[PDB]
Length: 585
Ligand SMILES: [Zn+2]
Ligand SMILES: [Zn+2]
Ligand SMILES: [Zn+2]
Image: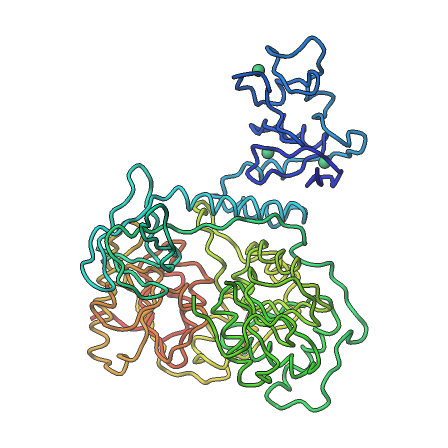
């Protein structure tokens, strides 16, 4: 028994075929079953033929006879079919409304999540259907990680490097840091965890959580976690106020935060507010400062990643009483300078999925482009606040959608919050970049921020761009462009100063070749989001939808404090770089 995800109508019927078993009222259960392949129907029992060794599970071919379900064949003299009168049989038959359309629910219940148009629906549908989609997608995502075969240690060539043997008759996952494994050791009658790991082509390169002397027989699987059903919406209902509510502003603020005094007051005058922070516009400065502006205010700082939550803690550690902070951790090595798991503490820094049920004066959700609607509904479920602030930049990278292959995902579709910022604008905007030379700012200002991003720094005169297609080899699930790494080898010799630079590319295999040949440190664009370096050497590697995505391109070039070389495959972005052009040697 539960609530029809379409009507809210009370009902005893869940679709069995749906991987998430939504409650469907007699009306909506029927409209669903007769318009799709989904025909299994669960109640206080499962609508299946109780007859001995009959296989009938379709509800359009079944009948209640006595108190037991039968198909045409086995039914007793006296029965009625489970499925007629535009309705499927179960409790609460007289309270049951229906819906004009069920089209969106069928699409969501049935889509394989490989087309972008799927995720577009999950983010424009009714809010109840945004929750059902969020679950159905996340459960599809965790199911797909099972389709992958087991990796097993066949030899230990060295430390940091291994020989893996793979389970037969199953696909092998990509070996980049978007695929985190879990290890296992072969015990008398079962198996025990031995840390989380990632792998990269060599033999394979493994970067484990802990260290060990892991030996042959030890194996690896992408550990999947049960997706709990969702209840809270992705956003609370918005309220706009005429005075600051529930918060007491400080009378003396420092000049370090004086620029955010207006925006912090806005936060006090609406239920939730959205802050776009472009690269190095000072989001965490904003987040921590809000505390000092509302000194008595209880604030729970959250993001999806440990990394994100830890950076909030690192800034907190500068400005806020340590004795007033606490980091929440469930039973990976994060920040460890705050008393651990003290929920009643004034400032609580915690990932989404480890949040405790609790209230708070303000909730700050950071790095909001990386959040799914699923995370969005967890935060609303776990934290009842007077005020919610969503901080991020819908021009930076979303969560990877492992299943997605047909179409690109536009920022207005990353989650409900980024939909808002792209369709009615963001409530607040950090509009001065402190990090990058002006050439890089001028470029992303135009590219993705409507000429509203302003450069604190001057031109560096150290931002260069080369058009060089080079040669694109492909391996198992990445790209390589050695001639582009070639160009950069040649550049470093004439420009030795740039031997301090980080190497950034949209591919881990490009990154691996580049480390061997240049011995620069490497980040993929995805792994660089959040970090800053003085000098950056970016090889686009390909002209793919991946390598040309304007959000990835935006994060790639905004890592530089001083100077950047961009070796470019794409004429389009090449032509949009406000950088000094260089000929090819
Ligand atoms: Zn219904
Ligand atoms: Zn279904
Ligand atoms: Zn039967």
